Image (spheres, helix red, strand yellow):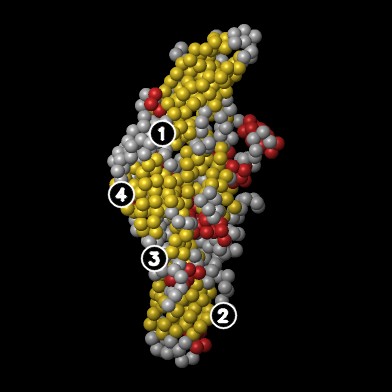
């Protein structure tokens, strides 16, 4: 007299209440520690409510071997005296034939796929349906709790990311589709997590982020190939290709996508995450605070590079409490893969040099605090020290701002101001702990931050003679192409000036930096390493200076209305001026964007001669309400993968009859 006809999980309503509406309207995705409502339908009318209520019990199971000691299986009754903090069910509305039941999960429940099962006394267990349980940044008792709604929207719900690339002095923001609410990302993430066998620890955000980071780094090492190859469409195709092997592989010039992929997996699981870019990052030192750079007599590097390099840019940051640490380390944690295992490092441990809190504090501290030493490499084979400009590491630590497409500088979270008292104290304490455990010429190099592609720049070299006697200096200037990770790509240009410097005189030399004078075109994704080396007389000391120059491509201007009505046609015009020296040939323009365009559309447009302007218009109809983003990519024979973006807020239609 108590048979069960069906069970409505009400996935649409619950997913909207549990901030999983972008995932699905059919499957139930709920966040732990928050009630969700199901409707239970009886085949026959229920005569007496209270005895029937006493007859029914609910069981929640996750995993292949669910048990109560693993906290993977919980049995609870349907009554108003259930523990709302724990697994509990209560009837909130009822009819003769249907019970509306509020079901609560504990704030520290194990995440993953769950089966909800109903037991009637003296009857077999019945499966009511499935649901997936995620971390809850909205729940104050949850370890991933975020104070601000804006921060929850940015670090969990926002699928349109910005990854900052380029150099410190020319930061190029790349539109990136995290796609954490793409339909299969949650399943892929949980299947990747199932490689770890300590499912009782899947309630802990620290353990999940540490496991996923080690697994994703292992997949990056297994799948990223040596070197369009550089055409990217966000984290989701990369994750699919890493887990399955099917799809376009990523090549080593874009190995920085690991941070974005990790951000996507964590955000999909419910852990707030952000992608952070650090410019001039000292990698591969093993905690050592010295970087050795080697240059030949022409201000150029002969080899591929040392193991310890200063990368032009290089991270995933995740938000959670740190219960197993001393107090005060809640908040932002850096996932750091070690070749392997993954350590979660609190950012303040890096800022305050708390080397010994976690095993990876030393390496993360060295990446943004090392000093570069430059050695001249002679034809004799001598390796000689150089008076060198200071090459600062850890510059312009950037991540996407909250609630806009702007760039937020977070460097002050990782480091005290240079030359300040606190930085002095931290560096002295770190150096002391490490120790216990174990000339007349001046060169000033002025360069532009960026060089227009197929364009011209002017560089300045200031030589000041401090001697009482005039000097015969040899000024070697070299331009070389470097990959983002400091790997030498191609020698481009070299000059050898011979100057006479008057005693006690400042001399300024201006040099034209021209693309057309380069011996070969810089490879794609590379940066210009400009060097100046001054040798005088027989002092054996060479003044040296270096700068990283970005390559600036033509600006892809997108003109679109700020507001747009859903289901009404919208026009976006795109303009691109050919500032290059050659016509743009084989020209393809692509448009995409979640909630604006299904997948993407590629178009061909006519060749654009130098000093001409392309102007393409596109009509499309937005179909999804909210803050959407249109991404436009332009390819030609002169350049490829030139992307820009623009945001449009899509409003619902005006209510009428």
* Residue 356 in picture, x, y percent from top left: 61, 42
Identify the image quadrant of residue 418: top right
Q: CA distance from mark 3 to mark 1?
A: 40 Å
Q: CA distance from mark 2 to mark 3?
A: 46 Å
* Residue 516 in picture, x, y percent from top left: 38, 26
Q: Name the residue carrying label 1.
A: 453
Q: Residue at x 57, y 25 (%)?
A: 389
Q: Name the residue carrying label 3.
A: 567
Q: CA distance from mark 2 to mark 1?
A: 70 Å
Residue sticking out furthest to the front: 612
Q: Is 37 placed above or below 210 here?
A: below
Sequence-first tag of 3 and 1: 1
Q: Is 324 placed above or below 362 here?
A: below
Q: Are dots 4 and 1 in contact, CB under 8 Å?
A: no
Sequence-first tag of 3 and 4: 3
4 or 2: mark nearer the eye: 4
Q: Name the residue carrying label 2.
A: 80
Q: Residue at x 62, y 43 (%)?
A: 412
Q: CA distance from mark 4 to mark 2?
A: 61 Å
2 or 3: mark nearer the eye: 3
Q: Name the residue carrying label 4.
A: 603
Q: Residues within 10 Å of mark 3 (few under 14, many from 20)?
A: some
Q: Residue at x 53, y 19 (%)?
A: 509
Q: Is 22 placed above or below 544 here?
A: below
Sequence-first tag of 4 and 2: 2
Residue sticking out furthest to the top: 469
* Residue 211 in picture, x, y percent from top left: 47, 51
Question: Which quarter of the figure is the C terminus placed in?
Answer: bottom left
Residue 224 seen: no
Sequence-first tag of 2 and 3: 2
Of residue 574 and residue 182, the one placed in the foreground of this image is 574
Q: Secondary structure at mark 3?
A: loop
């Amino acid at each position: 007299a108590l048979g069960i006809k069906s069970c409505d999980f009400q996935a649409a309503r619950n997913n909207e209440e549990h901030h999983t509406k972008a995932l699905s309207s059919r499957r139930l995705f709920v966040r732990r520690g928050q009630p969700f409502t199901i409707i239970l339908y009886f085949r026959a009318p229920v005569r007496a409510f209270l005895p029937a209520l006493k007859k029914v019990a609910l069981t929640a199971q996750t995993g292949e071997q669910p048990s109560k000691i693993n906290r993977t299986q919980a049995t609870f009754p349907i009554s108003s005296l259930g523990d709302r903090k724990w697994w509990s069910a209560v009837v909130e509305e009822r009819d003769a034939q249907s019970w509306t039941i509020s079901v609560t999960t504990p704030a520290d429940a194990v995440i993953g796929h769950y089966s909800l099962l109903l037991q009637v006394s003296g009857r077999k267990q019945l499966l009511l349906g499935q649901f997936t349980l995620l971390f809850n940044p909205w729940n104050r008792e949850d370890a991933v709790f975020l104070k601000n709604e804006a921060q929850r929207m940015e670090y969990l719900l926002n699928q349109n990311g910005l990854i900052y690339l380029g150099t410190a002095d020319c930061i190029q923001a790349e539109s990136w589709d995290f796609g954490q609410f793409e339909g299969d990302v949650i399943d892929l993430s949980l299947r990747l997590l199932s490689k770890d066998k300590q499912v009782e620890k899947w309630s802990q955000p620290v353990h999940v982020a540490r496991v996923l980071g080690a697994l994703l780094h292992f997949l990056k090492e297994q799948r990223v190939l040596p070197t369009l190859l550089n055409k990217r469409r966000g984290s989701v195709p990369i994750l699919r290709q890493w887990l399955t092997g099917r799809g376009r592989p990523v090549y080593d010039g874009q190995a920085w996508v690991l941070a974005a992929v990790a951000c996507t997996v964590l955000r999909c699981l419910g852990i707030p995450a952000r992608v952070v870019t650090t410019f001039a990052s000292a990698q591969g030192t093993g905690g050592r605070l010295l970087i050795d750079e080697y240059y030949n007599e022409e201000g150029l590097q002969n080899g591929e590079g040392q193991r310890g390099r200063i990368w032009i840019f290089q991270s995933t940051e995740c938000w959670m409490t740190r219960p197993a640490l001393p107090q005060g380390y809640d908040g932002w944690q850096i996932l750091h893969p070690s070749a392997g295992s993954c350590d979660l490092v609190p950012v303040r441990a890096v800022k305050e040099g708390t080397l010994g809190l976690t095993p990876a504090v030393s390496d993360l501290f060295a990446a943004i605090n090392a000093s570069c030493v430059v050695w001249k490499c002679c034809e004799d084979g001598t390796l000689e020290l150089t008076d060198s400009n200071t090459k600062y590491v850890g510059n312009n630590i950037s991540t996407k701002g909250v609630g806009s497409d702007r760039c937020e500088d977070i460097t002050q979270n990782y480091k005290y101001p240079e030359g300040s008292l606190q930085e002095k104290e931290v560096l002295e304490r770190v150096e002391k702990e490490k120790m216990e455990r174990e000339s007349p010429l001046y060169l000033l190099l002025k360069a532009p931050s960026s060089l227009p592609l197929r364009g011209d720049a002017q560089i300045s070299v200031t030589l000041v003679n401090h001697s009482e006697q005039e000097k015969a200096v040899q000024l070697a200037i070299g331009v070389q192409a470097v990959h983002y990770n400091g790997v030498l790509a191609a020698k481009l240009w070299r000059k050898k000036l011979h100057l006479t410097l008057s005693a006690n005189l400042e001399k300024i030399i201006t040099i034209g930096l021209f693309f057309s004078n380069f011996e070969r075109n810089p490879p794609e994704n590379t940066f210009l390493r400009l060097t100046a080396m001054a040798t005088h007389s027989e002092s054996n000391l060479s003044c040296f200076a270096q700068e990283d120059i970005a390559i600036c491509r033509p600006h892809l201007a997108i003109k679109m209305p700020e507001k747009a009505e859903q289901y009404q046609p919208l026009t976006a015009s795109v303009s691109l001026q050919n500032s290059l020296d050659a016509p743009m040939e084989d020209c393809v323009i692509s448009i995409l964007g979640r909630g604006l365009i299904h997948r993407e559309r590629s178009y061909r447009f006519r060749s654009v001669w130098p000093e001409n302007t392309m102007c393409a218009k596109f009509q499309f109809t937005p179909t999804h309400v909210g803050l959407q983003r249109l991404t436009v990519e332009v390819d030609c024979n002169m350049f490829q993968n030139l992307t820009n973006y623009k945001s449009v807020t899509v409003v619902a239609p005006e209510l009428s009859a």
